[PDB]
Length: 94
Length: 68
Image 1 (cartoon, rainbow over the protein chains, first blue to last red):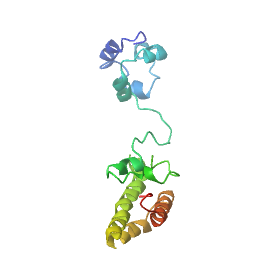
Image 2 (cartoon, rainbow over the protein chains, first blue to last red; image 1 turned 90 degrees about the vertical axis):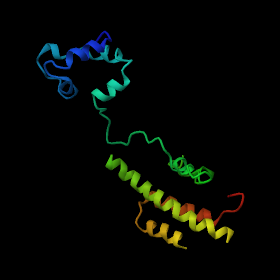
Image 3 (cartoon, chains in turn blue, orange; image 1 turned 180 degrees about the horizontal axis):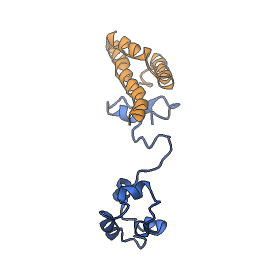
Image 4 (spheres, rainbow over the protein chains, first blue to last red; image 1 turned 180 degrees about the vertical axis):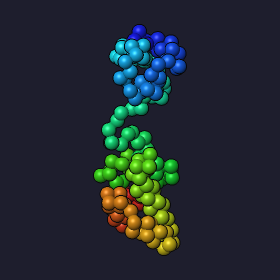
């Protein structure tokens, strides 16, 4: 894992002490085999975007996450009704 | 999710009030239920979203072919 080969890491951690969801939540398992070097594996888990997203929930604050549609934008699905032609004082109509 | 959709709800409400207002405005050019449809939807909308919509209505009142 720390070396980057998270494939064997997950394969060994599927049915081992602590467990994957436990590691997702709890890192206090005194079993030394249920822990890994965090940054080495993490930055070394580069080819695992989807795996990283699925394994551990993102501990974001209560602020809203990315909203990839704008009021003018989603409105533009009605062709001339793209609210960019006016309402420049409103950012949501981006 | 639902809290996120709650923000989207006012937007959906804004989306809900979006279509009705223009439809009343649309026929009123080439020439009322649509107007109240927004207005009724506008009676029960959020703060900043509905203020923005009212500003848009004012613009619609102060628009021309170029502004079109």
